Length: 101
RNA sequence: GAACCUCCGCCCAUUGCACUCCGGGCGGUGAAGGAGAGGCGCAAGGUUAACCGCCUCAGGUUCC
Ligand SMILES: *NC(=O)c1ccc(-c2c3ccc(=[N+](C)C)cc-3oc3cc(N(C)C)ccc23)c(C(=O)[O-])c1
Ligand SMILES: *O[C@H]1[C@@H](O)[C@H](n2cnc3c(=O)[nH]c(N)nc32)O[C@@H]1COP(=O)(O)OP(=O)(O)O
Ligand SMILES: *Nc1ccc([N+](=O)[O-])cc1[N+](=O)[O-]
Ligand SMILES: [Mg+2]
Ligand SMILES: [Mg+2]
Image (cartoon, rainbow, N blue to C red; front, side, top):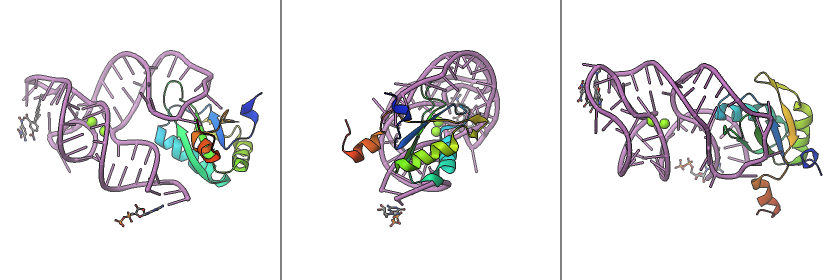
């Protein structure tokens, strides 16, 4: 019904500072999120449609859940992070589960 | 082995759920001057312009 609240390998963060550059944003996200588990990948775009947002993809769903709870609202580049679970599996995960396309 | 990046900014608009990239406008620096190198296009065309795209490579960084 509301998939953004059902745990997922991938967390969706928005309300990020759009001023920060793509690579710096990716590496700072990794720095703050890697202690919660192994990170398959972190996807950021500076597109009009995708700026201010990032998908952080964990190997273990339990890792996503701990990262979200612990970093909900956390100040990051002067804006409180807003964290959800991704509404659908990231492609790399769909490939693992055998569900891709 | 993989991913991301590789000239420096300003303003306007945007709170947006992607996984092939992709809003608009304006400046500056550098003559060891198209932005790490090569190739190939494309651009440019003299007091000081062009500043881009693709592919390969290199490096930096984060990982496996
Ligand atoms: N090394 C070369 O083969 C070479 C380097 C630089 C120059 C050159 C210019 C070349 C082309 C230009 N336009 C097409 C407008 C302008 C150039 O401007 C300069 C300016 C200066 N200054 C000392 C101010 C030096 C060299 C320039 C060339 C060239 O053929 O002129 C070749
Ligand atoms: O193709 C490289 C890869 O197969 C293996 N290698 C090197 N470093 C690696 C790593 O950090 N992770 C993984 N998974 N695999 C790695 O070695 C091959 C060659 O790499 P080198 O840069 O060492 O090449 P060299 O010519 O020096 O032997
Ligand atoms: N190297 C060089 C310096 C300056 C100029 N110039 O025209 O001013 C030209 C060259 N060149 O190589 O032709
Ligand atoms: Mg260039
Ligand atoms: Mg470049």
